[PDB]
Image: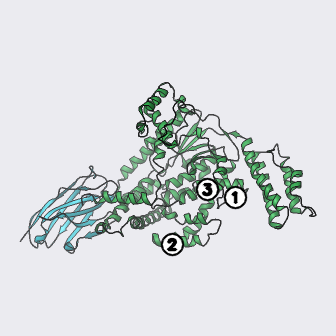
Amino acid sequence: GMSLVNRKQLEKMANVRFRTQEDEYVAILDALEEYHNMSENTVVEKYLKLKDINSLTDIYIDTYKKSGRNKALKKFKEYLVTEVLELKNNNLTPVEKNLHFVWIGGQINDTAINYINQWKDVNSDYNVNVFYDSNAFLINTLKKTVVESAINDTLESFRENLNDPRFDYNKFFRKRMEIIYDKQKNFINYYKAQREENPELIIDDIVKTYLSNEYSKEIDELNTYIEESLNKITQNSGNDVRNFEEFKNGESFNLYEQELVERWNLAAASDILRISALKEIGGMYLDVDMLPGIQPDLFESIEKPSSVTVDFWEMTKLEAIMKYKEYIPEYTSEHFDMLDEEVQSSFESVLASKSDKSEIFSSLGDMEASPLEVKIAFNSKGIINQGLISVKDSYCSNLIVKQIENRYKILNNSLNPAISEDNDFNTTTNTFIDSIMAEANADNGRFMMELGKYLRVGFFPDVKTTINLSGPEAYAAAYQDLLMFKEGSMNIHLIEADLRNFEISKTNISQSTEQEMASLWSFDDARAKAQFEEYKRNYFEGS
Amino acid sequence: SNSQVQLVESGGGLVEAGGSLRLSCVVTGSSFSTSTMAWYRQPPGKQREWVASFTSGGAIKYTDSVKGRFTMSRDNAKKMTYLQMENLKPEDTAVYYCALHNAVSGSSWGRGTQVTVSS
């Protein structure tokens, strides 16, 4: 029977002859009995009761480390976990009909708009938010300007050493960062001084003057870009972060601004915003490179040739749609054009027999989920926060937000003092890592390892800090928090099968899109070497 | 190479040994302020050689044979670079070219300006 054991059942299994019932044991039985009388309570209340039961059980095992009932109580703890999943699957509430996209730090491009429009076209019953920051359209411009200039400065120092094997990609990225870090410090010191002098100044005011003073950019041209950026986003369901009061007043806002203003990491700032948006409003978050799910039975008459993978086939399906329906102009066909004419004709025939977009892409419709959960997309590498589904104020959305805040607290506790010493990049790194390592233990070891690379994020190969800070790891940790009836998990022991309990159905997203499959590029050593080599070729052309 | 960037060098000619000469280069396009500017020269019979560079970060370098004699400058507002040559020697005779170097948007070169030093 799937239902959680009752008091009498627990008494039997946790029975030890000749042992009196301790106060700590009775407490468990009492709470278990209370749980079974809670049929009229809310899901969250039921969960909190289960949490209390687990806590009381842990207190017993810790108090009487030798007790004969520990074996049975450990089995009981397993039953509690199963009950959480049962509670999750059996009590569903409607998901608010909102689609959330995020595009901050610069002008939204046409490709993003075209993808978003696909969702709009088949989900007319959904409100669409494309979150942007009206104060910070120039952050990407700033980063690109600083980085490009730094690349060019660095390569000039390589001029007489191009055949020297010591002047490798490693040296390049190291030397480049010395310059980038110095500029980042210069900028943030300027930002802080400007804010002190005139608190009415917004990010873009300070950035544009900085760009004019430091890199001879024209304020007039930057003003035009801001205007064009604002107009483009507001005409495409723009939702300004600067009007998101709950976000601005919460404990995540300073983390958002840390990433936006100090680190110029738009991906990380997006990570922080998206889950706060989902928590506060409810609905479905999507990356702008996701497309609506294909109708399940659309291509059932076409079977896959043996000379191609599932990933090749999935990409081909979308490319066929875009070739013959032209929903997105300029969509690739490189995978479709590799097929035999017999199957290309098979695609053309199927799609010709279809009239409306609603016959090709499915609609999200009435969705429901547990008040406990956030659902997440999966790819071949595991969970990925490119797709999220949650009811407003779901327990897990709260757990995820808290995971991210706690991770940043650990980071900033060591990072801020390190930075404040006002040394160069390498010295700051060493100070920071030494500080982080002093707080490392068996529980947080792998996490702390990645944290130590924070300042390298986006500028060096083999850096996974973001996923550990604001990305998938924080989500896995929240799921562990839920299933282990705790908060602040650092050591992820959950595996795929555990996480699949929270998966978004494959029918609800097309993940194998042109934009996505191009962004599965991983910045590893090989990629870094190739990038260095491309930079050198461009830079030294002529002689 | 970046086709949207053009460079026009000027100021070359015939000059006496020990004399001074200033070359100029005007640059078009929008990459000047984030690029490195460089001067080169191709002496008769020999391959083109590097002379001087001035990075967008403000670093100046010179080839050894020219140190103490040549002065390179750059002006982001005017999008111009200059090579001031002093105490000119016969071995300085060459076609002098200017280049904008950019790893991101690409590099562009001028067609050069000839300098002949008498002796």
| Residue A175, placed above or below residue A270 | below
* Chain A tint as drawn: green
Residue at the location (72% across, 45% down)? A88
**Chain letter for the residue marked with disc 2 in the picture:** A
The alpha-carbon separation of the residues under discs 3 and 1 comes to 12 Å
| Residue A178, placed above or below residue A41 | below
Mark 2: give few (<14), some (14-19) or many (20+) Cα within 10 Å.
Answer: few
Circle 3: residue type? Ala
Please name whichever residue, A123 or A352, is drawn nearer the observer in this view of the structure.
A352
Q: Are marks 2 and 3 on the same chain?
A: yes
Secondary element type, mark 2: helix
Residue at the location (65% across, 40% down)? A95
Secondary element type, mark 3: helix
**Chain letter for the residue marked with disc 1 in the picture:** A
Quickly name the residue at label 2: A430
Chain identifier, cyan in the render: B
Q: Is residue B114 left or right of residue A404?
A: left
Quickly name the residue at label 1: A487
Q: Position of residue A491 (x, y in %)?
A: 65, 61
The C terminus of chain B - image quarter? bottom left
Quickly name the residue at label 3: A474
**Label located before the other in sequence (2 or 3):** 2
